[PDB]
Amino acid sequence: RSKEISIEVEDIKDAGDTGKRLLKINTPSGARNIIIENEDAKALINGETTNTNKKN
Amino acid sequence: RSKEISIEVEDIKDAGDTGKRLLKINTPSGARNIIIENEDAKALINGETTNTNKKNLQDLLFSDGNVKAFLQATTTDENKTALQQLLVSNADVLGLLSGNPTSDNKINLRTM
């Protein structure tokens, strides 16, 4: 009868929507895409800014 | 096989690598260390920036190189010429600010 019963993210009944997205994410870039909504701030944190991002 | 299901993070089969690291983390600082890969951006968010972090953040924030030199408080004579042009529109006054006005600038500055 198995040994571990590896649950999945959606089995965690009091996890939040952003919380489940973060738990599923594999890389730091993916996490930043979830967490940072302001596109200019995200661009700064990614070290990749256009002239429009810089002005903003 | 059953007492209670006090599962652990690695029992969650479809959790991602970053997702499991975040679920295990205890503090906001730890979470920021996982999520933010750019060291200059992480330093800004932590409110703890070196002069190198500041210069690198200025590179992410501003496109104009003459403006960037001004913000670093280190300007060449070429940077100064360009910055003068952002600050003053009169061509004869720009001649004066250069320290080397042309003959025409000199005549016009006296008239002025």
Image (spheres, coloured by chain):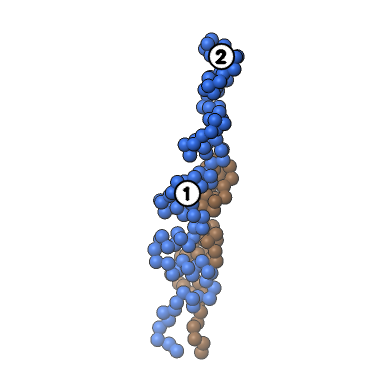
Q: Please provide percent x and percent y for residue A21.
A: 51, 64
**Chain of the residue under the numbered disc 2 shown in the image:** B
**Closest to the observer, B10 or B90:** B90
User: What amino acid does circle 2 point to?
Assistant: Lys
Q: Please provide percent x and percent y for residue A7.
A: 50, 77
**Which residue in the structure is indicated by mark 2?**
B106
Q: Secondary structure at mark 1?
A: helix
Residue pictured at 46% horizontal, 74% vertical: B9
Disc number placed over residue B53 in the picture, else none: 1
**Closest to the observer, B42 or A16:** B42
Q: Secondary structure at mark 2?
A: helix
Q: Which of the two discs, 1 and 2, labels the residue nearer the N terminus?
A: 1
Q: Residues within 10 Å of mark 1 (few under 14, many from 20)?
A: some
**Closest to the observer, B85 or B103:** B103
User: What amino acid does circle 1 point to?
Assistant: Asn
Any idea which chain is the brown one in this picture?
A
Q: Please provide percent x and percent y for residue A20.
A: 49, 67
Distance CA(mark 1)–CA(mark 2) = 44 Å
Q: Is residue B1 visible?
A: yes
**Looking at the image, do the residues carrying marks 1 and 2 touch, with CB atoms under 8 Å apart?**
no
Query: Is B40 rendered above or below residue B78?
Result: below
Residue pictured at 48% horizontal, 39% vertical: B72
Give the colour chain B carries in the figure.
Answer: blue
**Chain of the residue under the numbered disc 1 shown in the image:** B
Q: In the visual, does B110 lie left or right of A14?
A: right
Query: Is A35 rendered above or below residue B108?
Result: below
